[PDB]
Image (tube, rainbow, N blue to C red):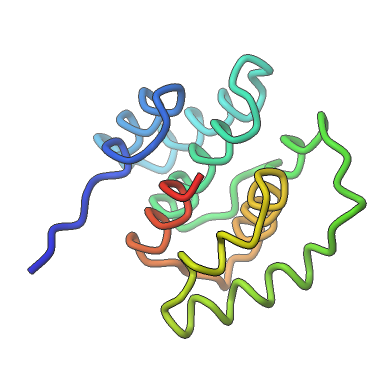
Length: 136
């Protein structure tokens, strides 16, 4: 009975224009262009780009082309993404991702998102994507 908010209602302001555009016109070609623009913009920082990426992944149901490139400005060798993602998968299965995501700092969350989006077999529902982006 609880409405699902839109992604554009919960994302950060900087990601909002891109997310509106993808939600309004979920054509694969259009969404791929929007993703590729924000991927490449140094002017959208990591968290902003990750929210655009998460919504692209959800709407397109495709791996976002080249998404690992958005980690070019950060050192990520101090975490273990394979382990983070296995834990995240578990939390999704038990309905506790919101609480689990509290255990990650900002970089860990963003790193996790890139790894999640690169995996064509993960299929978050809208609420789980909303959990992720509103948790940032």
